[PDB]
Structures are given as structure tokens and as C-alpha cells.
Image (spheres, coloured by chain):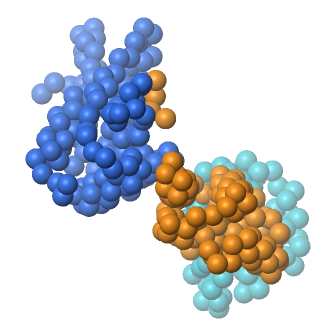
Chain colours: A orange, B cyan, C blue
Amino acid sequence: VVQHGVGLGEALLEAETIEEQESPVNCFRKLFVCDVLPLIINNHDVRLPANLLYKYLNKAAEFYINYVTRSTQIESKRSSQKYIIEGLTEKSSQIVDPWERLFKILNVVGMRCEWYGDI
Amino acid sequence: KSAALHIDLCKATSPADALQYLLQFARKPVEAESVEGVVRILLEHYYKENDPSVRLKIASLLGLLSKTAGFSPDCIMDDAINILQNE
Amino acid sequence: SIPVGISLGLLKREMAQGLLPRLLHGTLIMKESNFRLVSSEQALKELAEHQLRFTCRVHLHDTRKEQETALRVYSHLKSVLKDHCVQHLPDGSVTVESVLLQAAAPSEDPGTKVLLVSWTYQDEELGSFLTSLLKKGLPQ
């Protein structure tokens, strides 16, 4: 990903086009975005330019929007939600704490540049 | 003639008359292709309707259809576990 | 035995917690020839209900950064707590039972780092014991 640089966005666009589903509300797109974010979160030494950071922020925003609500198209405590997967069982999407993933992505971004109520 | 069952179910009012129509349809016998159609119609109306008792009756009829000897219940099992996750 | 009533929501939550260590609070009001228990949220219906919450400050002195140290603390706690934490919060905060741990900047001093933690007495005793255990010895 680091060597490719700006090619990650083009690869993601090509993958989305190949999937024959332009709308990114599908659970597969959100899962792929989360997986891409964890890879960047794992390596904190991978510095990126302004364009790459903007693209990553846009992708994270799109993934969060998709995760918050998904289209209804068809053809001791815990937190979770519900949705309908595209041609697969809803239990197949094994994703835990997307908000924590966003927090980890923000942490990795801050780590690169050395950075009433509770929040 | 699945069309007759479909149109009769659609014309039936949701709260009360639907229960009586489903009971009357349940008492009479059914055939393999007729089962394969009415199960999907029942699932669609189960999604559409949100009353507790009606959904309970639909689940009971799903159980009755599953006991049919000649039927091949494979896809309806998948839909059953899906609605189980959603129930 | 003293006969009293319990709010349905509290009992439902208690049964859900028991099904899958946690202890339940108790708040009751003397009534006319009877006694009734009521939850904290339901007790607010008596309005007035002026809620006061304590927020003690825990001070630490270390040259390490904040976010990485927070991640290390989260890993250490989730290892010690035998995976009792299966929930997360969006702003990099981890909560156990009913105590919130979040990163907050100090008021004016840049040379010292301070965070704010709030808890009840039942959580206060456990928090004090855990902080004393941490201060006893760590790989520092």
C-alpha cells in the first residue's frame, strides 16, 4: 500500500466496479474499508501525504456512513446493530466494534504526526 | 393455483380475517409445489406484518409445512435461520 | 423477611447480566405502611432530583505519550480482567462495569499530564484497590 501510494483508491474503485454494486452501503464494502484501515493502523511508521490522508478520511467517513445505516435492498453489556447483507447471512459479517476501528485509525494518524460529561 | 391463494390472502384484512383465512388454508391439505409457493408467500407476509399473534401463527404453519413428507425443505431452512436471527 | 417491590427494568437487566459477578445496587423510599425499591433513573420521576457525581483525579508522571500508553493500559486491563470487557467506545475509551476511562488534556499546565475519572463508592473502592495494585509494581 505504501509503495502504491495513490493507487489504493484506484484499486478500491476498480474492485467496487467489478463487484457490480456501485452503492457502498453493502456490508462487504464496509468490511473491506475496515480491513484497509486496520492495515494502516498496524504500521504506524507509514507516513502519507496530504492527498493520501484526505482519501483515507473520505473512505473512513463513507464506511462510517454505510455502517450507521444500510439500504433495505434485496434480490455485562455489549453494543451492535442490524442490517441485511448482500446475498449472504448476516452472521457471516464478523466485525467487532467499528467505532473502535475508527478510533484506532485516528490514533495511527495522530501517531504518525505525534498528535460536564466525558468526551 | 397459487394465484387464488395469493389474491385471497391479499384481499383478507390483516388484523383478524387473516388469521381465519390462514387457519382455513392450514386445515385443507397441500401439495409439494403448493407448499414451495405458500412458504414464500407466508415469509413475505411475515416480513410485512408486525403483529405478535399473526407471526406466531405463521411460524406454526411453517412448522406444519416442515412436517410434510414429500417436500424438500432446503432453502426454507435458510430463510428460517435468517428470520431466527431477525426474530 | 421485608416485602418490597422491584422495578421491572432493573430485574430484567439483573437477569440478563446473571445469565451471561456483577452486583446490583439498591435504592428504596419509605412509603405509607410499605417499602418500595426504585431504580436511579426511575427515582428521578419524583420531581426535584439534583444529581451530584464525584470525579477524582489520578496523577501519573511519565515521559511516554498518551495514546500509545492508553492502548497499552487497555491491553493490560483486558488481559487482567479475563476478557470481561466486550464493549468499546468511539472516542478511544474503554469502560468496565460503570467507570469511564478517557484521555483529557490538563487545564493550563503543559509540563504535567492529568486525567479525570468518575465513579460511585462501590466502584471507588475497586478503583482505589486497582490503582494501588498498579502502583505496587509494573514493568516501568
Q: Residue at x 72, y 87 (%)?
A: B32
State the residue in front, A47 or C22.
A47
Which image quarter holds the N terminus of chain B? bottom right
State the residue in front, B70 or C128.
C128
The answer to whether A13 appears left or right of C7 in the picture is right
State the residue in front, A31 or B7.
A31
Based on the displayed image, in which of its 4 quarters is residue A1 positioned?
A: bottom right
List x then y, in percent, for residue A31. 61, 69
Q: Residue furthest front?
A: C111
Based on the displayed image, in which of its 4 quarters is residue A22 positioned?
A: bottom right
List x then y, in percent, for residue C116. 35, 31
Q: Is residue B70 visible?
A: yes
Which image quarter holds the C terminus of chain B? bottom right
Label count reads 0
Q: Residue at x 18, y 58 (%)?
A: C139
List x then y, in percent, for residue C124. 21, 32
List x then y, in percent, for residue A13. 79, 73
Q: Residue at x 46, y 28 (%)?
A: A117
State the residue in front, C1 or A58.
A58
Q: Residue at x 46, y 48 (%)?
A: C92
Based on the displayed image, in which of its 4 quarters is residue C43 positioned?
A: top left
Q: Is residue B19 visible?
A: no
- A36 lies above or below C60: below
The answer to whether C113 appears left or right of A2 in the picture is left
- A75 lies above or below B57: below
